Image (cartoon, coloured by chain):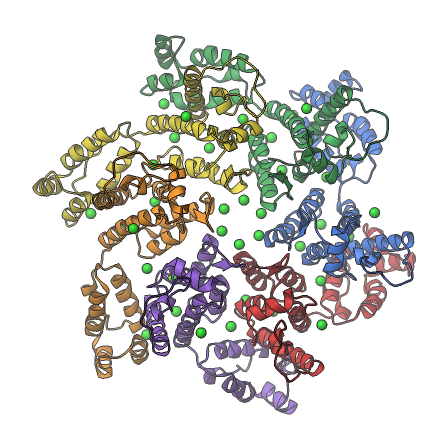
Chain colours: A red, B blue, C green, D purple, E yellow, F orange
Amino acid sequence: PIVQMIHQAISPRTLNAWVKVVEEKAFSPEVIPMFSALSEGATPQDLNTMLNAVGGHQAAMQMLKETINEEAAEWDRLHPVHAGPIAPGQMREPRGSDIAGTTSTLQEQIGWMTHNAPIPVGEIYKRWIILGLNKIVRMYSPTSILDIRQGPKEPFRDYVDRFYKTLRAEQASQEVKNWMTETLLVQNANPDCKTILKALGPGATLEEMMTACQGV
Amino acid sequence: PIVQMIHQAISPRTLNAWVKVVEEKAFSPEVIPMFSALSEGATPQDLNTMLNAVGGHQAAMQMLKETINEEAAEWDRLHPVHAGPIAPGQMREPRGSDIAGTTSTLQEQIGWMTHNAPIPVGEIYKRWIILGLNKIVRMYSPTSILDIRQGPKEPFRDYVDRFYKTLRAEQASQEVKNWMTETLLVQNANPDCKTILKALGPGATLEEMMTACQGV
Amino acid sequence: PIVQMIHQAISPRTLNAWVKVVEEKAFSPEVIPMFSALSEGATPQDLNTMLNAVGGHQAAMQMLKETINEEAAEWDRLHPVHAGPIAPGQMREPRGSDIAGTTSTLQEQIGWMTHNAPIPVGEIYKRWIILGLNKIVRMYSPTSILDIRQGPKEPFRDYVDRFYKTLRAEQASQEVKNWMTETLLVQNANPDCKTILKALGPGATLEEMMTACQGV
Amino acid sequence: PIVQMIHQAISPRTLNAWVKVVEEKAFSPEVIPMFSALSEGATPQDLNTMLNAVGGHQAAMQMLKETINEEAAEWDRLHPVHAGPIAPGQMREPRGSDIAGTTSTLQEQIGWMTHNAPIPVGEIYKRWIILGLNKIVRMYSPTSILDIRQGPKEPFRDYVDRFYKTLRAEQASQEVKNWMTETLLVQNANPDCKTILKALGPGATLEEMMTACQGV
Amino acid sequence: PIVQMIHQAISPRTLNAWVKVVEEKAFSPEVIPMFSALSEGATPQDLNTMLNAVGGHQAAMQMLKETINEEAAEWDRLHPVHAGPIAPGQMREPRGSDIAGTTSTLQEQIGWMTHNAPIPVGEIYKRWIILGLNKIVRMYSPTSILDIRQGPKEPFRDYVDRFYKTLRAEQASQEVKNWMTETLLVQNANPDCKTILKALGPGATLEEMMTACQGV
Amino acid sequence: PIVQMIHQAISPRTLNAWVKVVEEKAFSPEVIPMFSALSEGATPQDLNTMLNAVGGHQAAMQMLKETINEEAAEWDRLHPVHAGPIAPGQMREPRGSDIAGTTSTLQEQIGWMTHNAPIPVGEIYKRWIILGLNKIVRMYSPTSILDIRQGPKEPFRDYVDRFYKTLRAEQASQEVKNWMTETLLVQNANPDCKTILKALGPGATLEEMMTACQGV
Ligand SMILES: [Cl-]
Ligand SMILES: [Cl-]
Ligand SMILES: [Cl-]
Ligand SMILES: [Cl-]
Ligand SMILES: [Cl-]
Ligand SMILES: [Cl-]
Ligand SMILES: [Cl-]
Ligand SMILES: [Cl-]
Ligand SMILES: [Cl-]
Ligand SMILES: [Cl-]
Ligand SMILES: [Cl-]
Ligand SMILES: [Cl-]
Ligand SMILES: [Cl-]
Ligand SMILES: [Cl-]
Ligand SMILES: [Cl-]
Ligand SMILES: [Cl-]
Ligand SMILES: [Cl-]
Ligand SMILES: [Cl-]
Ligand SMILES: [Cl-]
Ligand SMILES: [Cl-]
Ligand SMILES: [Cl-]
Ligand SMILES: [Cl-]
Ligand SMILES: [Cl-]
Ligand SMILES: [Cl-]
Ligand SMILES: [Cl-]
Ligand SMILES: [Cl-]
Ligand SMILES: [Cl-]
Ligand SMILES: [Cl-]
Ligand SMILES: [Cl-]
Ligand SMILES: [Cl-]
Ligand SMILES: [Cl-]
Ligand SMILES: [Cl-]
Ligand SMILES: [Cl-]
Ligand SMILES: [Cl-]
Ligand SMILES: [Cl-]
Ligand SMILES: [Cl-]
């Protein structure tokens, strides 16, 4: 990565941490924040390093490759290369593959990131990667939000844990997720807690809901 | 984080330490100091990194989200955005969502924190987070302070351990906690140690109390 | 902490090291040096961080709180606040609670420590903490120095280990501890080694004593 | 290594990380990215350090030696040494063995890398090493891409994992690997999923294929 | 410690390393080099930190205290304090107890070490400590060099291992240790290897001796 | 060590790494590269630190001492000390024992290494140590290269592993090792693979040999 802006090689414990995360957590939602944290200020070479280090899950890594290629293609369509030689004191405009790090040197990436009025190639590539990771997380989620229902003997807190876990994996905008929270959560609770929740009303917070069904 | 003031990426072992703390300790009181220590000088992006890295406890993390949104809303009510373009050499006033890091870039956060006469967005957001964490710790505490009572064969020291643990989780100001210490502790001790404690008087320190019932 | 003088956030492995030390070693004497070593150059915020991170032993942590409050009160009596506004280029005199870090900001602590003709708030608070830790170590020691006696089949070296361990926990000045070393150690040895030790005389060193009873 | 450009000794945890990787992962594809990441900015002395540290797999390490010697020989043929004494302010042109680090000092390597209009000896040597590593990975792969076939009860995702693992080990250009992906993957699937995949058509993405046979 | 010269707090892993070394290795010879390595450039406060951190072996730590006091007393006899006030730009001459760190501040130690024409208080104290450690290692060694004898079925290499281990613990100058090597080693070997060793002669090296009795 | 050139104390994890390497790997060939890597830029004090830290293998450490003394003696014969006082701005020429670090201070070593037109005492001493380590590795190798022979059911790759391991331990120049590779390897293979190898010819590479007997 580059830290203020000075280039640093990716540390062994950062890379190991990411590898271990992929092994232990598969493609759980929390891996995406983790990834970002382990790739803070990272060059495209660092990001490719993290992805390539993963052994196994090669179907998911291939899907990630196809997503990255789609994003690179869209970038190329939006940003067409301009003919003519590069002038001194200037650098060539980055193609999609340069952002992915496959066709650009480390010095070129450093140059784009450090130069005044910069192009943050690492952050763009990072966005593409996180997009594909979201695709993978959503496909690999077994459960659907509609199916989560509270058991008759199940404590409300556990039910809310399951519900919001599944919700975190769901493919939906924040408006849709809001609708799910304010529609399905109370509807799918068990009858005792469901009645008690209905009694609270439409504006009840999560804290009030969990406190109300705490005894239940 | 930012260390003197120079921005640093959150270290892998800091993040791992926080994750492990959440796994092992759930929502015990000591997690809140720990959090602070692991977030010293942290940007809103770092704080969101720590929260988002948590897998599981999604009910608590959702409660935390609602608390953060309430605090952001109160901030927005107190600090209304002013119309007009931002001048050169100046930065826009931060909204509630910018303090939470959801709507502000890393460079904007760094700019607010580093600039002369700064706005410490990381510390404000950190306060909101710790507020919600206090809500969660208090709700997730099974015991109540009134119920802690010394067993007849129970050594006084163990009883004081239980008492002050439960007290640490309790929802009360320092005046109320003072009243609890000076009222309930001696009252709920077992009869031998309770008599001996009554003999000491109202001004007896904790050290004197534990020394007096040490043989008992 | 602050290292030369430049402020640094408390490292995750320092804090973890202290937590582990409290868990494994309880309140053995060696925890107090350890504490100091883990708090070298630490601000009051760092010290509070270390204390607050401890889970359990809440009776001892409460005793520590009462000791810190007594020391803060004595400081306040010795150093009375002076009326009048603080001038530019100067900082307010620290109250007891400011030294304990409960009522002072991190920037205020840094300012006191870094400024020319400084007030070392971290070292003062550290002294208070170590004082309370000594109270706790002494109360939590089960054994008394008078009771340590050499077994008939017990090797002298083991007996000296037990003796000086208990002595290290004892509540006594160096003059009293000297008297204990030169009175009780030889007196409480077993008859064979006790006779041999008496034969050496009053000025015999520990090395000579252990060498003399090595065969015994 | 050298980090910006300042020379650094190879860290103990980098070297240990590489050694552990060779032990645990043998010669799986992911070891080659790992190697690169652990050798970022490394001098030829660092690279030789990493290779020489490996215990066991001496057949593979010998193959690696022969590949490095072939690459050094080709370099020497392309770059013939020029007679005449080296001038002040200039350094001798590197031979193949100098790039491999066997015949060049650390100061010479540092000089080539740091000097203006530099020769990156570490990156050239690194390319040779990675070339030989590719030879070893390909020879040590037991499976062939043609043999990977989906089981009748085998979930499609597992089959795609096996397929792309074997493909990653395969000795083929990206055009050939493209042909394999678009020819053999759908052909070697089981009849239910194979029929469903045929129904999608030639332009179907991996995500669409896995989603389509997800129920299957 | 102080590293070039800039003061650094003792790291948590250095201290932990020393503690673990004392636990696992007791007072084996190799602990003394280890100690030195963990105390490189250390102030008297750091050295006291390392000694005080040790739990257990309190007889040995007390012996160490008596040795340090003897060395401090000899220093005081050689270096008598001179009456008169300390001038500006100058520092007081260190007493024995100041070198031991018991009566000197950290700033005083730093001042002695950093100042031009310095007094290396840390290295002097370190010498005293290592002297007492040698006393302890020698007393705690069970074996004597005269007793080490080769078994009839014992391989020569194992016998040389035992011999030089015991020799390393022995209390003797290098001239005496030379005499022991050139007298007792060949004399105490078993008859087959002893005869073969006698045949080599008085000037035979250790390598020649081990090679000669390798088959034996 | 010294890193660019600035002196650094040997890290705890470097030393621990070396100790663990000696414990686990004994005197396998790979320990010698490891040693070098852990001693990069190290002073003679650091090298002595690493050697002295080893517990056990005292026969080998003694052999190492005799080798170092022989190398120091040869250095002294080649470099005779010159009579006359050392001038200001100059340092005394190093004797053999100074290079070994037994008779030279840390400041003297630093001075030799840092000064313009330097004497690299650490690298010279390091060469002596590695020489003695080679003696030890060769003596402690049980197997001889002539004895390695392929089993009838033994896969060729395993046989090449054993062969080149033993070869790595062998006492021979690169010309002799070349002769062994091109004479004994094919000769000692089993008859099926030996016939197939003979069919390839004298110029066959290792890769071709292993590929040819892969089915065999
Ligand atoms: Cl690292
Ligand atoms: Cl994996
Ligand atoms: Cl999965
Ligand atoms: Cl790859
Ligand atoms: Cl953009
Ligand atoms: Cl519940
Ligand atoms: Cl880290
Ligand atoms: Cl968790
Ligand atoms: Cl919980
Ligand atoms: Cl997230
Ligand atoms: Cl504010
Ligand atoms: Cl008690
Ligand atoms: Cl750390
Ligand atoms: Cl604890
Ligand atoms: Cl306890
Ligand atoms: Cl707290
Ligand atoms: Cl004071
Ligand atoms: Cl004894
Ligand atoms: Cl390291
Ligand atoms: Cl290996
Ligand atoms: Cl393999
Ligand atoms: Cl080697
Ligand atoms: Cl090139
Ligand atoms: Cl599937
Ligand atoms: Cl550390
Ligand atoms: Cl111990
Ligand atoms: Cl012992
Ligand atoms: Cl102590
Ligand atoms: Cl001196
Ligand atoms: Cl032998
Ligand atoms: Cl370290
Ligand atoms: Cl060992
Ligand atoms: Cl061995
Ligand atoms: Cl030694
Ligand atoms: Cl030389
Ligand atoms: Cl084979």
Q: Residue at x 46, y 36 (%)?
A: E39
Query: What percent of the width, then of the height, locates residue A96?
Result: 64, 78
The residue closer to the viewer here, B133 or D178, is: D178
Q: Residue at x 49, y 79 (%)?
A: D167
| Rendered position, F181 above or below F122 | below
Q: Is residue F172 left or right of residue A115?
A: left
Query: What percent of the width, then of the height, locates residue F113?
Result: 39, 46
Q: Residue at x 64, y 60 (%)?
A: A40
Image quadrant where one finds the C terminus of chain C: top left
Q: Residue at x 43, y 36 (%)?
A: E35
Tell how many labels: 0
| Rendered position, E120 above or below B59 | above
Query: What percent of the width, then of the height, locates residue B168?
Result: 75, 37
Instruction: Give the quarter of the image for residue F57.
Output: top left
Q: Quadrant of ligand 34?
A: top left
Q: Residue furthest left?
A: E199
Image quadrant where one finds the N terminus of chain C: top right
| Rendered position, E11 above or below F5 | above
Instruction: Give the quarter of the image for residue F207.
Output: bottom left
Instruction: Tell me, yes or no, if residue C140 can be seen here.
Output: yes
Instruction: Tell me, yes or no, if residue B55 can be seen here.
Output: no
Q: Is residue F192 left or right of residue A75?
A: left
Q: Is residue E25 left or right of residue B38?
A: left
